[PDB]
Length: 338
Ligand SMILES: CC[C@@H](C)Nc1ncc(C(=O)Nc2cc(C(=O)NC)ccc2C)s1
Image 1 (cartoon, rainbow, N blue to C red):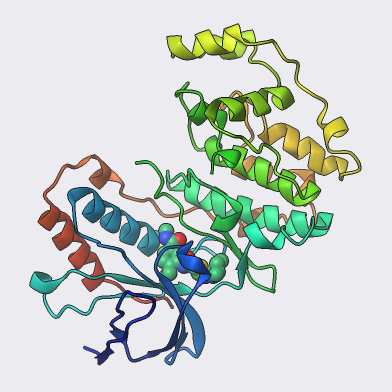
Image 2: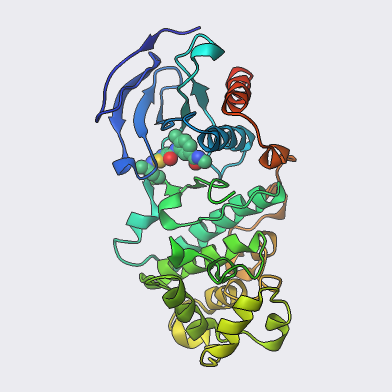
């Protein structure tokens, strides 16, 4: 065991091992109860997240178990990984707190683009890294579901890591329409749509689709990608959806080259491949990585897939204490990095 140390930041109290000094409440709890700290053992700066009421209900206990499992699985340069997970409980019996530790990233895209648009080479390198991380997560059947600029962490290096993946469900500005509009089905390409919206924002400096709500959002998307065609409506299982869609004013798809003027045309062609309404036609992360727009960074031999990930628990309906014990088991068997 290690020697812990109490303290109270904001209003919450924190009990971490002594190897973690200088805890300072980071990014307005936007990433949750996270503190920046110094790793006395690695001499590196890490981010410390104390889960909020980890086992108050079944649902919380399940989300806690889900989080730990996901973080323990992530072993990739472009996806946040687990440096350490600890609890101040000497027993499963008194296990009520969870703390997760990852590398500390400098900033997130929600702010850096808020300093005016980016250069094309900056977009190539950032979007490239997102696609590499996405290729890895999707290869394990994990979907981020809420890819957003504040969910993309970068260092001064422009080194990029995806965060907060696979938590959402089982903001709308970046959401794929097959999620907005009722639920005409979907897949992992729901993340590609988000990357499309993000890339667009980075290139222009403006929110591609600044929706006011679900209906205003959809309306903004169709204006750009156009009204759903016959091949698309043929695949819509939702009678509800087929009504709305087939009833609103028919809009043609616009010329991206005209909407994104002066942008690297290679970039425009890629945006065309990501921003398609039909989720079966959207480009994949793996395919996108081979897009000429990334000629300068692409390397098939260094774009790894992930080991398989056991998501069967997702289907289980257990008691709070059973999720707790499972979480406890996961904390216990944790094996740090190299
Ligand atoms: C980019 C924002 C700036 C302020 N720095 C940051 N570095 C790292 C941050 C972070 O959230 N780490 C983190 C992410 C997850 C996660 O992704 N769970 C699925 C879980 C726990 C932690 C501790 S935030």
